[PDB]
Length: 66
Length: 69
Image (cartoon, each protein chain N blue to C red):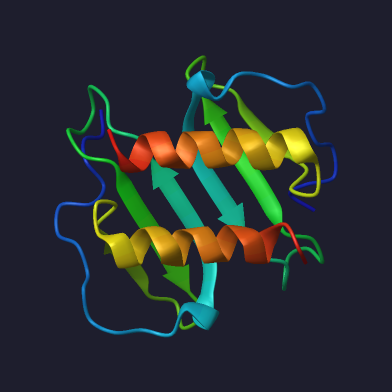
């Protein structure tokens, strides 16, 4: 699956440059959240995790108003 | 090497329940605009305007849908 090994350490939303949310289906039974950081890394995050929900929301708001 | 990935944005009605993937690319040196691309279950990809109020709600709803699966 795309989100087996997720990244578990909190970081500031300012480093997120792209967001991809993939719905669970023919590929994985889990909904995937993948971020591309300014340093080039693509991390899978756990959408149930609270810090992830806050960080993703912050990024979205910024991207929609930038 | 790539530039903007969303020059023209889609505004025709569609069913949000068909959204399978959402991709948000913030503006920067590559593209003056933020791109919101959604891929539907019928294989279509629509670029939507991030400044449009109805688009923000659609994206917001899909996220919530994500963290509650």
